[PDB]
Image: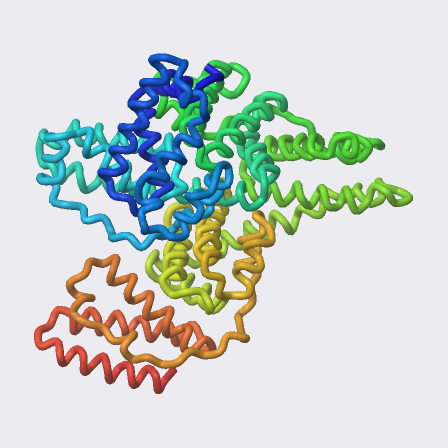
Length: 581
């Protein structure tokens, strides 16, 4: 139980989940170690766990699993020449070794793209040896996303195995492996982005910000529960996410399972939508728990104009317990406003706290904090107007032209950012309105704002490793709920000097013809970024015309033979375009 925690985790999780989580953690710590070494290490660790559970008396079983994992790491690929910076920390002792391991994670490693072999030969390996294939999939997915959510990865591996075991042999093997695998990889990428948001926010801004976010989201999702129940759920969720985001995986999965069991047991006092999918295995049950839809609010709640303003001793209560009072206010406000974004509710709570602090010690506190609710009008009006105009622009322009427009806008805003990361950020920003602008004018704001925040956190975390601009970091490290107000309030950067000209970058080849549509669009957008950076003062219509003619010739002289004529024509066009800005 409490003694020899490895045995406790082995009983609570089981051999299969134990091995899977151990492999995931090993892959996440070391991102260049070969697969065979990872499998051998996992087998050794699980054999040691079996020995520990067989007899709870061995001296090594007393030690925490953390130092055991660290010691097993410092056996191969860590002290063996490679990873010189890791070898220096490998010689250190706990808990400094764990800190070095966590702070050395690479968000974007220099690793080859997945090959995706031919379907028949790909799942004939599954038919030959399913366990090795699943382990390889887990290792490959954990490599590229060191901050991915492990129980979600277990669920993804389970569904992946289900897909192969159902229709690798039935009929038309491609008819599964195109759509099902594409959907699975898209969902995995989205979950990786969300979990990176959560871990980055927690690590950067402490657990108070994460507690506030959890309170807001849980109260939005569970508007019928009492404050104590929501606080208990928030505490459990905060502990779980702190465990996963700090490199402790097994206990994180165990606590997630415990929380899911508690919620599906206490359904009666939480909400009414949980009845649908508590009668199913653990992994997808927790998947519901982390994804269940909102619930209808209680009928005829108070107006909040008597519980937070009219009371004479309101900030006497605030000073009695600041955190408790702010949590109560945030819970009530998110309960009464399910159509507001989570970050918007956090911003409103911050504004309320700021004004309450600014006016509770003057002559007449009420004279200040009487009109507190009237300051929320612009704070909620601005995002609604911005999303309205964004949907207006996107609907009549199409996804690709929306990507181009967002790309030119954010290239004007922050030119110093690197070209590929800027292209990726703009692509995701366009995907925001591609995915959840079709909603009615009652649910656009939550999804739109949340996905915009996710994409902007991706931008900040990609830029942080190589700080190059004096504004992106300046207010990506300012506030967590003030990233989108930054990137929507940034002015056109006139300080940026024009870049030098390089006709080789703009020149195209037959690769644009031999590649798919996605890589073609990516190359065109990269050329757009370079063109905008070269001439930052060009009007939007000029850029639109230049890219329209760009598409024109790349669609005209791609299909034709004697490509040298295409090269000469595009070179003369480049000369003309540089002459005409």
